[PDB]
Amino acid sequence: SYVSLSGLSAAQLDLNTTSNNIANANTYGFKESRAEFADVYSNSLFTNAKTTPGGGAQASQVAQQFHEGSSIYTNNPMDLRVSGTGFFAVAKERLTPQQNELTRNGAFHLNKENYMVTANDEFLLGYQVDPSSGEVSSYEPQPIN
Amino acid sequence: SYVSLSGLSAAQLDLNTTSNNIANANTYGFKESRAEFADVYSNSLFTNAKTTPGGGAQASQVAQQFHEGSSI
Amino acid sequence: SYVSLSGLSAAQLDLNTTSNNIANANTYGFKESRAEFADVYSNSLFTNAKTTPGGGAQASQVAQQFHEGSSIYTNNPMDLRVSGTGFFAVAKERLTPQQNELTRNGAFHLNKENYMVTANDEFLLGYQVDPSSGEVSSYEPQPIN
Amino acid sequence: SYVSLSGLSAAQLDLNTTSNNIANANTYGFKESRAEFADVYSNSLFTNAKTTPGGGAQASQVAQQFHEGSSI
Amino acid sequence: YTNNPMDLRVSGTGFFAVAKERLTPQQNELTRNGAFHLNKENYMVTANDEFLLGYQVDPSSGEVSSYEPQPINIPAEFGKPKQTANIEVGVNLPANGDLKDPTQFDFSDPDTYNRSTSSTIYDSMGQSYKLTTYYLKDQTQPNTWNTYYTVTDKEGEKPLNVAAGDAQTPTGHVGHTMKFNNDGTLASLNNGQPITSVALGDPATNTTPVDMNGADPAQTLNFGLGSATQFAAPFELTKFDEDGATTGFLTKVDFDENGSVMGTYSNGENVTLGRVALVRVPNEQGLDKKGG
Amino acid sequence: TQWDSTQFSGDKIWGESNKGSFGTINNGMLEQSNIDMTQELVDLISAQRNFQANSRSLEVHNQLQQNILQI
Amino acid sequence: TQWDSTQFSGDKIWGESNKGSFGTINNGMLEQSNIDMTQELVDLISAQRNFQANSRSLEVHNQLQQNILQI
Amino acid sequence: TQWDSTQFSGDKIWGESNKGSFGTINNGMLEQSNIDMTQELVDLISAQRNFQANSRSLEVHNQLQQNILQI
Amino acid sequence: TQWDSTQFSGDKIWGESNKGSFGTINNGMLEQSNIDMTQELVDLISAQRNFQANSRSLEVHNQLQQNILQI
């Protein structure tokens, strides 16, 4: 009966993952999830093996498939998209660029201090380029003003 | 089931935003609105992460796109 | 027969725990309970051990699994939810903030005195911030007005 | 069984609240109601606590959400 | 499956080891259930508040040093600001870069050197300091580079001298030299000597002592540049690793297959709290059965 | 659709229109119910589900008691 | 169709017409809504599709629960 | 749905929101019960099965004793 | 829709746009979900079918146990 309960749990986990994927159909920059499972088997010291059935199914991991999604056009230049490999970097607080998180959506706007932030007013990390030389001198992240 | 309910709420919010934009098609000086959403995920102290699915979709903000409109 | 009676008692305790969990399915901020049991065995000075059977099953504890539950959206800003680790603090009386209890539901509303209270008119404990400095000066809890 | 009966009572109270909200869909100026419930636990002088299950669910209050309604 | 990571199961042969009291790990009993939770002292205990016995692993080495069983503790704070001692830097230097005069090096003039990089370091007390590294391409010797370091505190930017670096500017600043083979790989570093800097805040060894503001003045930095290369590619900071740390709070805790209980804090260090002891007896049929 | 002031509510604070914390008065309009049919129907479904679960639990309790009765 | 200055917006910066970063003022013209009917209708269709998909998911969840109920 | 700090729990540690190990606070939301109806129903069925098995064992014991009695 | 770097993920490698292995940055666009509704709905149907099959198996196990009980 526990094997059947494990099967029910795995099926409901896949159902929940699919429901989350469907619900996030409109979220910007969202990446879908995939449910992968694995077989279960005992490893007792004295195992008959030929006379021992399986032990059900165990959830292995919920994947985070990162294949490129489609792009919409809003004609708003403050909206940015990373085509290819790479993530945007945003910091919770302006004065602590060290504490940062990665994101993909580009719904940016200027706050009252003329800094580019996300919807949650999280500052967008940027570099500092040289006045004449195109190459960026310092690679430390800082908020863009 | 609450994930599906969150998806329904997000879809209905987008529907309402679009309906408001369509209704205000003749109002002078009106600026359209855009509905932006975000994912939901728990941050429990003891989180399995790999074995934990998503938490639905949460409304982030209703934008106020201020791009210049046409002139009559 | 006492072993069978212990088994019956344990099964009925688990049944009651499950019934309570099902009954509280709609309560805001509720945390489920899990019933855990343990074996029973004698510890006599002169025990045959090999020739002595078990002593039944005894309830060990009723757990209070505190894993984060799902969230509903009501579009009522007076409703609050703690995402992650943390509890709200509520005081029975306004004048005795020391006497307080922890809770998780956020059904708050202004009473006749413009204080944020729960359903049972229990005042919500909060800090007092500096006018200019964001950091809270005094960490003592006081009712929010 | 009394815990199950309390659960039935709470579910039926929520059902009645929803029915009233649906019935008053056309009444002018009506404000919806929300059902809020709470847990029950004993406070005996000698309580084992670790070996005591819950006491069911008790209806706390029927709210009167006063958020602005639509205008015709 | 309860999806509660504090619940553990021994798949195969083995028993959990639990002690009646924290201070007496010798008095222990074997069990199989894994209903674990932190007590008020942040120790993993069973339902009966019996401490779970575990090992103590090395900070860097995965192998456990001492096999004696001890209660497992999960601190809620990384309460030990760790000073930076070893910094690993891997860069690629431009082979086509313009040559510079070794005697004309000056960190105040950008045109005298080739490239400058910035990084953050921590002292004993956890104060953050800005570390700037200046790379200069030698003109006299082809495939030779000069590296200098400076520390910028609130007082100003003070140059840092190497204990045995073979690059002495006329001003007095001491750097180290890097040489590369024909294939562009790394040939030698500071004439084969390890790169150890002078004490930051000790005037007895530094002509420009760094203002520690109460920190340890004898702090020393060891730079590991074993992956530095000189190719046709432009200047690039490929890798930067340090051993510094700052105060932080417990964020999440997980268990690997080896039984090591790992926890990540706000600072970023993945501190391994310990391992979970496993006990196996030759004849399991003869174990006496206690309660629970 | 009328309310009165109780002890918990407080005391009636009188005021004009568009003064202080009060709102404005618009003629030619009326207020509808502040309900959402989608939310009400989904809540109805969820409440029915919970009621069925509780009835199942009560049936299990009664079945256990009757099983003990037949000894 | 009126807005006010809040904390997030900042503070009102006053100025003249065609001065600094401001625009110009033309008489005899009015602003229409800055919307595109085509995009609004397409978004309406997409939102309906998403709502139907989510309703299907919720129906599947309820059917699973009812199937378990009948044991 | 309220808790208090006891000897085993420890002492209450006060703090702000989104500071240290604390979480965040969101307005406009409420927390539901952290239960899964499927798991609860399955556990209910299993508990009923265990109770029936124990009742069977008790009946066996009583029948054996009565069989001894009729000698 | 934000991520952080953990032990398994590695360490954050910074870079510019259209340099090395990084991609390009296009303004005026946004990323949608990288999902396919058809695949999600078909997976939903398949998962429901698997759940029904497992529930049938559990019911068979319970029926066998209850059949043994009545001896």
Image (spheres, coloured by chain):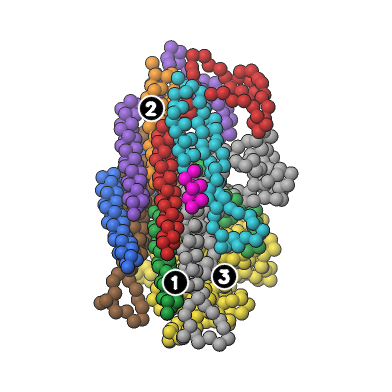
Chain colours: A brown, B orange, D cyan, E yellow, F red, G purple, H green, I blue
Amino acid type of the residue that numbered disc 1 sits on in the rendered structure: Asn
- Mark 3 sits on what residue? E48
Is residue D5 located in the magenta-colored stretch of the structure? yes
Q: Is residue I27 visible?
A: no
* x, y percent for residue A88: 43, 48
Q: Nearer the viewer, residue H39 or A57?
A: H39
* x, y percent for residue E149: 55, 63
Under tag 3, what secondary structure? Answer: loop
Q: Nearer the viewer, residue A123 or F43?
A: F43
Q: Image quarter for residue E126?
A: bottom right
Determine the chain carrying the residue at label 2: B
Amino acid type of the residue that numbered disc 2 sits on in the rendered structure: Ser
Label pair 1/2, CB-CB below 8 angstroms: no
What's drawn in magenta, residue-wise? D1-9
Determine the chain carrying the residue at label 3: E
Q: CA distance from mark 1 to mark 2?
A: 73 Å
Amino acid type of the residue that numbered disc 3 sits on in the rendered structure: Asn
Tell me the number on the disc at residue B19: 2
Please say if D63 is above or below E44. Answer: above
Residue at figure coordinates x 32%, y 79% from the top left: A47
Q: Residues within 10 Å of mark 3 (few under 14, many from 20)?
A: few
Please say if B51 is above or below G20. Answer: below
Residue at figure coordinates x 47%, y 31% from the top left: D20
Q: Is residue A6 visible?
A: yes
* x, y percent for residue B20: 41, 26
Determine the chain carrying the residue at label 1: H
Under tag 2, what secondary structure? Answer: helix
- Mark 1 sits on what residue? H62
Under tag 1, what secondary structure? Answer: helix
Q: Image quarter for residue E256?
A: bottom left
Residue at figure coordinates x 45%, y 55% from the top left: F61
Our reading of the magenta stretch's main secondary structure is: helix
